[PDB]
Image 1 (spheres, rainbow, N blue to C red):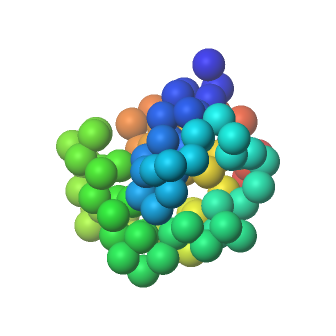
Image 2 (image 1 turned 120 degrees about the vertical axis):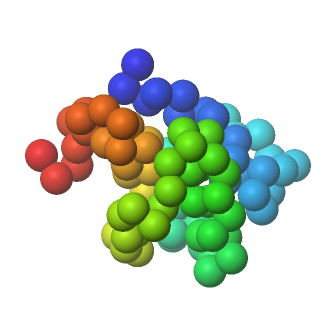
Length: 91
């Protein structure tokens, strides 16, 4: 369950720019930024829906470009916000 709905996260980024692509065909082992799917407005859209699902405000914490290091980090960031991080990359 470490993925915590990994396919769901890909579904948002996939639908954010490539909705005609099956999220299962995306490797979560590749950094999300390397794809370039996350842009300036793309970054805003990411926090807008991701924050809306948990009802949390991004203003409470500042996000850095490193937080977009990979989709895996996004799952940890979302979980880290409500519950302690699991196998965080830092540890």
